[PDB]
Amino acid sequence: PYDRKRQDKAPVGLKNVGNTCWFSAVIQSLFNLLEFRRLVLNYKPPSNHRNLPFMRELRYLFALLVGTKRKYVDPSRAVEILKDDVSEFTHKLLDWLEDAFQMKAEEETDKNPMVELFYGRFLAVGVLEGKKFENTEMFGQYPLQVNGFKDLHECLEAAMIEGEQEHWFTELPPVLTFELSRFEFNQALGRPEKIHNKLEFPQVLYLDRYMHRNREITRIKREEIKRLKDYLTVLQQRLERYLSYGSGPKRFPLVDVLQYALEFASSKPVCTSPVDDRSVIHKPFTQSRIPPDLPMHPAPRHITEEELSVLESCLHRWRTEIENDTRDLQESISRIHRTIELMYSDKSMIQVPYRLHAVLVHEGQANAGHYWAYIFDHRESRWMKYNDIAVTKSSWEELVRDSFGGYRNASAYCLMYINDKAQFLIQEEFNKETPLVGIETLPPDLRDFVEEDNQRFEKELE
Amino acid sequence: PYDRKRQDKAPVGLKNVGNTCWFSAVIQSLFNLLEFRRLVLNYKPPSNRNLPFMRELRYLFALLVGTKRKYVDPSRAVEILKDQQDVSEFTHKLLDWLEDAFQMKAEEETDKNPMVELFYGRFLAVGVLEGKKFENTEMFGQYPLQVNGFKDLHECLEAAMIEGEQEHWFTELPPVLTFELSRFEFNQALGRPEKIHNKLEFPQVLYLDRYMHRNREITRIKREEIKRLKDYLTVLQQRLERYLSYGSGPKRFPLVDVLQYALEFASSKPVCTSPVDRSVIHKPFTQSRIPPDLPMHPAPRHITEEELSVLESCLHRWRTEIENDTRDLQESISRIHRTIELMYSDKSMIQVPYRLHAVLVHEGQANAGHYWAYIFDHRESRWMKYNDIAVTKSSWEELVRDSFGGYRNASAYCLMYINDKAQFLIQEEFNKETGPLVGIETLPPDLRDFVEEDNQRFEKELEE
Amino acid sequence: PYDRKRQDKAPVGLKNVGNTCWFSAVIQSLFNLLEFRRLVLNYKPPSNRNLPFMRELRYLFALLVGTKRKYVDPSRAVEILKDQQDVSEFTHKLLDWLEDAFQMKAEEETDKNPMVELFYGRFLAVGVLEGKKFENTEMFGQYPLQVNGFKDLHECLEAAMIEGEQEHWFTELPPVLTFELSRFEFNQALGRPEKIHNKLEFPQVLYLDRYMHRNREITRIKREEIKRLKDYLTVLQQRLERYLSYGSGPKRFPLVDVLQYALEFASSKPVCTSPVDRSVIHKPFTQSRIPPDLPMHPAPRHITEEELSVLESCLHRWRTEIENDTRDLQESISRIHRTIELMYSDKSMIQVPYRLHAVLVHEGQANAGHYWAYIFDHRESRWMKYNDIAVTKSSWEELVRDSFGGYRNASAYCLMYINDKAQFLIQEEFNKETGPLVGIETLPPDLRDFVEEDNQRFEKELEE
Amino acid sequence: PYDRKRQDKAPVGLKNVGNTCWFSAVIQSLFNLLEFRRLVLNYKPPSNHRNLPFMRELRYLFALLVGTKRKYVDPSRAVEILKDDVSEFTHKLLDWLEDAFQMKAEEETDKNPMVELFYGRFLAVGVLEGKKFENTEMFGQYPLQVNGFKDLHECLEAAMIEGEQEHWFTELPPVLTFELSRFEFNQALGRPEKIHNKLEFPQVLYLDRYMHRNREITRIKREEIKRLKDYLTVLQQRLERYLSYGSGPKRFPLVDVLQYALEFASSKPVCTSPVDDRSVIHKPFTQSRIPPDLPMHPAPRHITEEELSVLESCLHRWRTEIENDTRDLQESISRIHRTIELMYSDKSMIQVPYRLHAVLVHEGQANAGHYWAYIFDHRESRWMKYNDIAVTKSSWEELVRDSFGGYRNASAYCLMYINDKAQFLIQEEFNKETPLVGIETLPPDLRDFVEEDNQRFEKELE
C-alpha cells in the first residue's frame, strides 16, 4: 500500500511484536550467514517434539524474508511458538535447532552441521593443587568480561588465563561467537549495573595467538610483554614526576614552574610596596602593539645583578635539561607501546583471520531494553543496521558509535565473526543459467508460498 | 473523613482544582495578612462581576478561618474568575476586582480606598533625557525588579531605581510592599526566553531608609562613594589575581607555589643518567616512617654549591615577600567589603524596618509551572510552607532552599514585606469577654452560621 | 638594635640557623609547658654528651624567659646535637639526652623519672594470631597514627588500636599525650612515597574515656554497634544514590528531574514540521514580562488529550512519591549520623578531657621541609603561631588553615595534648612577696645574673 | 673540536648572545629565501650611513653560514652593529636594508628589489561620513588580531572589513608577511596578556578571494555566508533545545530523560515503602550473568496496567521522533558547514596560491621571551626547526604543536608565505659544469674568507 513496499534488491524488515526486538536481531544475523539459510531452507523433518512446528515456521519465515516484495514481514507465528529471561529464551531456540538438525543425520557412524559451525574444542592446564590438568570442551559461545579492558584481545587473554589454568584453542568453528558481559555489581548503587567502559574490537581478528600450535612462543611472548609492562610502568611513573611535580596538593609541570620562576625573577623589580596605587606601513618582522614593559606588581624587590646571571644560567639550563628528559621518556614509552602493539604482527601469526560478520547491541536496563544488530552485506561490502523494520545502509562509523562502548548509551553484547579462509559460508551455488539469483534459491513449496503472498500483495496495493 | 479533619489550632489548606496552585499561594498570602482578612470579612455590598466573586471570597475566608476540615475548596470562587493560559493577568483580575469593589465603598467626602493605602504609594523621578528636568510621582504598586547579575536585594533595588545615567526616590510607601522578581531573560544558546537561575539573597527584614527622598542627599553622597570604593577595590582584585594565577602561558599557578616548587627542586640531590635505569616506643616529637633520602630522578644534573646559596636566599626571600603581599592585599579587600556592607548601618539609616511576611515561589516553565508560598506565622513566630492541601511548619532554611534559587528548580517570584513600625496589620483587635481575636469569633453572624452548619455536616460525615 | 627589642610581656622567637626551623618548633612547644620549664631551670648535674647540651638548653630557657631582645639564638645549643639530613632522629636525640639526664637524678629508692611520667604510659594488648592469647603492656611514648582515609582523630585512633580482626587498650596515660600523624604513603602514579593531603579533623579537647580499659566492655559493645549501624547506613546511601543518579546509560540524572522534565515536555504545545522554518503600575501579585506561549519546537507532534490526563496523573503522583522517598531516606541517614556522633556523648564517657596544647606542622618534601608550631597561650587564652623569629597572636581558624591539610601545603605532623584534670602543667607556683610566677623571677640566681648582663648589654647596644 | 663540527649538507646554526634568539629566527628565515641571499651576497656598496658596516657584516655572515664546516656561527659582530623594543629593533634592521638597497639602484627613471619582494598595494571604500573613500598603500606586513578567530581567513576577512571601509588587494608581493597579535587587555589581571586562542593556518593559502579582480562576487559570496550563518545559528539554538532540555538549572538530553522515564515506569512496582530493609557450554546468543530482575527501590507503586500501554506508546513514539529530529538537524548543520567551507573552492578561486615558507614563534612574557622559527627546506621538502644552534628535521606536527595556539605554551607571531606561481625565489642559477653547488654560490672575497676559516677550523680540530 502506502510505503509498505520493499525496494528492489533490498533487505527485508522484521515486525516487532511484544518486545520481540531481540528476536529480530538474532534471526536476521543467523539468516545473513548464507550457509545457514541454505542449511535450513533445505530442511524437511524426517517422517521416520515441539522443535518441528517452530522449525517449519522459521523456514517459511526465511523464504518470506528472502522472496517477499513487502518491506517487512511478521515473525509473530514463529515467535509465539517458542513458549516455555531473554538469555534462556534464545537458549531454547538454539537448543531446538541443534537437536532438530541432530535428528536429520542418518546412517554413517553416529556430526551435526550446527555443532560444526558454532562449536569447537579448547585445552586446560594444572589447577592449584599441584596436579596437572588436561581437558577439552565444546565452548560454543565464548563468554568475556569487559572489566577495565581496552580491546578484544586484552579481554580474551584475560578470559583464558583465569589465574596464575590457561585455555588454548584446538578446534575453531567457522563462525565464532563472543559474549561481552557489561554487568558488574555497583557498590555506590548496590545493584548490578552495566559498566560503560568502551571496548574496541577489530573488523578482522587474527586467532593464531590463542591456538595450541604456536603455544610455545605465545607465552614465550606473553611473558615478555609482562616484563615490558613491568618496565613500561616505571617510565610512566618517572614521566608523571615531570608532569605533576609538587610538594603539596596542587602539582604543575616542572618545565612550567621553572619557566614561570625565571620570568618572575627577570621581571622589572618594584621597590614600591603593594596596594599603593592612511595606515602605518609595517616592517615584515616587527611586532605591532607590543605592550609597554612598565612594572607590574608581581616582580621581586631586591634583585642583585650578580645573582641574576646565576638565576638565568641555572633555570634555563635546567629547563632545557628537563625538556630533553621528558622528550626522551616519551619517545621510549611510545616505542614500547609500538612493540607491544605489533609483536603479534609476524607472518606466522597472521595465518588465521576471522572477519567480523555481525554484532548484536543492546540499550537500556538489563532485564528489559532495546535490541538491534549490525551485519555485513558482502555483495555491496557495506555495513547494514537492522533494527526491527528498519534496515539501513549504516557505516562502520555508526557501528563504532553505537556498539563500541560509552558512546550514546549503547553497548555490544555479542560478536559474531566468520572465518575468511573458509568462504563457503557466503558462497552461493550455480544457478546454471548464468548464482543464488534470489527467490530461485528455495524449493518449490516455499516458491509457491512466496508467489501467492506477492500476488496477494499486488491485489492489496490497489 | 479518614485523615481529612483539621488538627486543632492549625492553618487550613486549599484544594488544587484545575491548576489552582497559584491561586492558593496568592490567597493564603493575602488572607494571612490579618488586617486584610478583617477588611474582607466586614464587607456588605450596598443594596440601596466583582460582587459575586467577592461574596464567594468572603465565604471562603470564613470557612478557612473556622473550618474543622483539613482543607477547603476554592473551586466555587476560582471558577468565578472567568475571562497554557496566562497566570499574570489571571492574578491581576482578582486584585482589580477587589480594589474596585472596595472603591465602591465610599461615603461622604470624595477621597480613600483602604487597599490602595495598603499596597501602593508614590515615588519621585528626575530628568536628563533631553537635558530637560523631569519631576513626577506615580503609584508603583508591586515594584518590579530584574535579578540579572545581582547578589542581594539591595543591589537589585539600586539598579531598578537608577535606570540610566533618571533615578527614582521613594516618597510614599504602603505598609505592604510587594517586589516582583523577574528571571525571564532571552537565552541566546537556546533561542528562547529562559529563567536564569542565579541565586538572589533577600533579608528577613529590609531597611529602606536609603531609598526615600528624606535621605536622598546622603545616599547620593554615599552611592557615588561606593562606586569610587568599588572602582578602587577591583584594582586590588586585579593585582591579587596576578599572585594567584601567575603564568605566561595557558596554564597559570599561584606564584608562591611556583617559587616553593622550584626551590625544593633545586634543593633535591642531583641524579645522573636521565631515563636509563613488642613495639618500638616512639620519641615524643620524632617523625615516624619517613621515606629515605634516595635521589629521585627529577633533579638538576649539576648544581654549584656556591650558587645554591644564591638560589635559596633569593627564592626564600621572594616567597616570604609574596606571602606578605598576598595577605596584605587580602586584608585590604576584606576591609573594603566590610565598609561597603556597614555603609548604611548607622542609626540614621536603620529607622524604617520592613519584616518579610510572605514569598511566592514558582517551579517549572514560565507559561505552566507549579506555585506555592511561604508565610510567617507571627504568633508562633515560625515560617510555614503553604502548598495546596499541605500546610507545614517549615523553617527559614527550607525557605532559602526554595526561594533563593540555584537550589533545585525553585525560584522566588514575589516578595511581600510588611512594615514593622505599624503592627495593625497583624493586630487581632479585642474581645471584652475573653480579655482578642479568640479565633473564629471574628466572623459576622451569617458566616458564623455557615461555618457551624459545615462543622455539623462534617460531624455527620465522620461517623460510620 | 633597630626593631629588634622584645615588646613588653610578649613571647620570644628563636633564630633560624642552618635549618633550625624544626628545632624552634620542638623547643618552643616543650618550653611553653610550664612544668617542663620549671623542671629544666631547676637542674644541677651532680659534681660529687647530655650535660653540655643540657646546660646550654637551660641557659637558652632562662634567656628566652627573661630576655628583652625580640629573638634569641639557639645556635650554641643546636650545634651541640652533633652525630638532607634526617630530622626524625635528630629530634629523637634531644629527647633521649634529656630523659637520660633527668634519669641520672636519682636518690634513695631505685624507682621515677619525671619525664617518663610526663610523656609515656602503658597500654594493653590481646592475642588472636595463633589462636593463642596475648596480654602485654608497653610504654607507647608518642603514639603513632596513619591518616590514610580518615576524617577525624577518633577514626584514626580506633584504626590505630584495632590493628587486625589484636586491639590495644589504654591503662596508663601521661598528662602530656603526643600523637604522631604520618601522611607518608607510597604513590603508585609517581613511584615515590608522597605525603597524602587528605584533610584530618582534630578537636581542641579530646575525651579518651572510650579508649581506656575501664570502659573496655562498653566500647566493645558500642564499637560493634556502630559497625552494624554503619553496615545499615550504607544500604540507605546506596538506595538514595539510585534516586539521585538514576539512569540506564553513562549519564545519570536525579529521577525527580527526569520525571518533571518529561512531564513538562508532554504538557508543551505540539509543534509540526520539525527543523523546517509614565509607568504601567503593577498589580501586587502579577507576573511581569512573562514570555509568550508560542509553541516552541521541542514538543510532541501528536498528543491525545485523553492520554495527557493519564500522563499528568501518573507523572505527578510519581514525582511526589519520589520527593517523599528521598526526604525520608535523607532524614533517616541524618538521624544515623547524629546517633553515631552522640554515641560517646554520655556522662560516663566524658570524664577524661585532654586540652590541645600544641601542634607541630610541616611544609614541603619529607626529607627537607619547613617547620613551625602552634601553641596555646593559656593566660590570654589565645592560640599563638611560633615560627622562628615570628611570634604572632594567631587564631584557631589559622590553626585549622595550616594544621588540617588540604589547605595550601600545610600538614600537622604532631599533636601535643595536655590533661585538664591536672593543671599543675600550667601552674606557676607562688611568690609570697607578690601575692605567682611574676615572670622572670622564676629562674635561679646564676641564670638571673646572666639575663641581667645580657639585658644591660642590650641597653648599651640600643644607644647610638 | 668536540661536537662543534657541521654535518655534511646540513643547515648552519646561529649562536645566541645576549638574548639574540629573535635575531637568529628572523635572519635564518630571510637567508632561507634563496632569492634574498642571492640579492645580498651580490652586494657591494657604491663608492659614488651606518647601513654599510652592518650590511657588510651581514653579507660576511651569510657566506659563513652558507659555506662553513662549523655547526654554528656567531652573529655577534652583526648583532652589535645594530645599535640605537624588539619590534623597533627588527624595524631598524629592515629599514637599513631597504634604504641600503635603495642606494644601489642607478640610472633608469628614479624600484628597489626589497619593496618588490615584501610590499604591494591595497584599496579602500567610503567611511561613515557619507563620502566615498579610495586609496592605496604599501602595506608591507599585514597585521592581524587573533581575537576569537579559528582560522587565518576569518582573521584576514575581519582585519579587512574594519566596520560596516573594506580593503582589497591590488598588488601582491612574492613573499607575504602576516603578523598575529595575541596581545589583548585582560580585565581579570588588569594587564595586557597574550591570549591563547588557537589559530589555524594552512600550508598553502589561496589569496584569490581578497583581490579586487573578483571583488564583485566575493562580497556577493560573503553576504551569502552571513545569511547562511544567520540561518545556521537558528538550527544550533534549536539543536541545543534537544541536547540541553530542562526547566531548571540542570539540563539533560531530552532523549535521555524520555528513555529514563520510560524505564522507571516499566520497572517492577514496589508497594512496600522505602528504607524498610568442566565449563558450561554457552548458547551463541544467550547472555550470561544477566542480573535477576528483582525489585529495586526506585520503581513506581501504583502502576495501572491500562495506563502502562499509554506510557509505552507515548514515550517510545516521542523518543523515536526526537531521535529523528536531532539527526535531521545535525545533518543540516553539517551540510551548511560544508558549503561554508568549500564555497571558495571553485577553480576561478584557486588561481593564486601562496605556499608557507616560514613561521616565527615566541614563548613567554611579551617584553622578553624566547624566539625561534620553522622554515621549509624545499630540496628535501621537509620542515626544519631553527632554534639558535639547533637546526632540526622537525615535522609539520611539531610545527602545529608549537605554532598553532594553546598547545604547550607557545604561539606563532609571524607568518611568511611565498608565491608558488613565482618560483624564482627558490630557483638557483646554473653552475654550468653540471646549480647552486653550495659554496660556489658566492663571490671570491667571501670564498677566500670561508676557505681560510675552514682551514683554521681544520687546524683547530686537532
Image: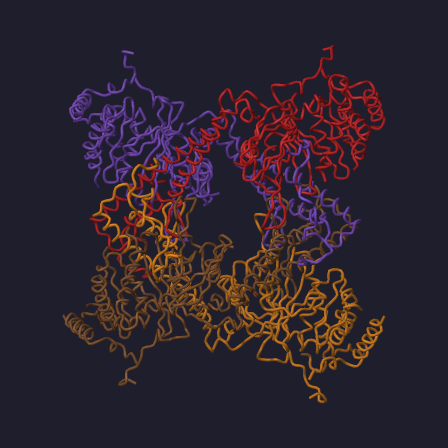
Chain colours: A purple, B brown, C orange, D red
Q: Where residue D35 appears, x then y in whole percent?
A: 70, 21
Rendered residue at 42%/58% (across/down)? B145
The answer to which of C43 and B453 lies nearer the viewer is B453
The answer to which of C323 and B182 lies nearer the viewer is B182
Left or right: D338 as drawn, with respect to D192? left
Determine which quarter of the picture holds residue B355. Answer: bottom left
Q: Where residue A359 appears, x then y in whole percent?
A: 36, 33
The quarter of the picture where the N terminus of chain B appears is bottom left
Determine which quarter of the picture holds residue B452. Answer: bottom left
Left or right: B305 as drawn, with respect to B350? right
Determine which quarter of the picture holds residue D374. Answer: top right
- State whether residue D227 is above or below residue D310: above
- State whether residue D257 is above or below residue A4: below
Left or right: D37 as drawn, with respect to B47? right
Q: Where residue B174 appears, x then y in whole percent?
A: 38, 68
Rendered residue at 48%/54% (across/down)? B149
Q: Where residue A302 appears, x then y in whole percent?
A: 76, 54
The quarter of the picture where the C terminus of chain B appears is bottom left
Left or right: A84 as drawn, with respect to A414? left
- State whether residue D168 is above or below residue B459: above
